[PDB]
Amino acid sequence: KDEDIFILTVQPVGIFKGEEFFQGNSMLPSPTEPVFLVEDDILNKIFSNEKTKIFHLG
Amino acid sequence: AGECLVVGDSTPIPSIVKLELPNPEPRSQSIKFHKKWSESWRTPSFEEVIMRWRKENG
Image (cartoon, chains in turn cyan, purple):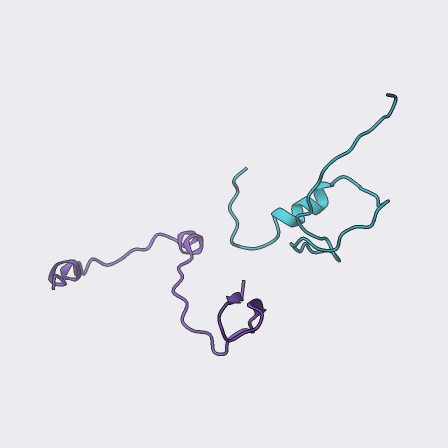
């Protein structure tokens, strides 16, 4: 009935306070708040990190 | 991590508590796999004391 609706259901898995990633389901964002996709710059910091004990698996 | 369920008759509300870090901390029976593998091959001289396996039968 001429009603363009595009609704996504997402679940928080962490926070990016500062420049480091913390886990936890807290700090609910207020309504009318931007969503900005994800860039590889923050994904690398979450996953690769920097430590001797690493193991590549894809 | 570091929190426990204190459920019993000695509390009015059984709750989860943020226990502080013990001092001094006990012995940790943990073996880390990759760092030991990261070193070169362990070359054991063969004193061949399998009497560990043998004589410890009773």
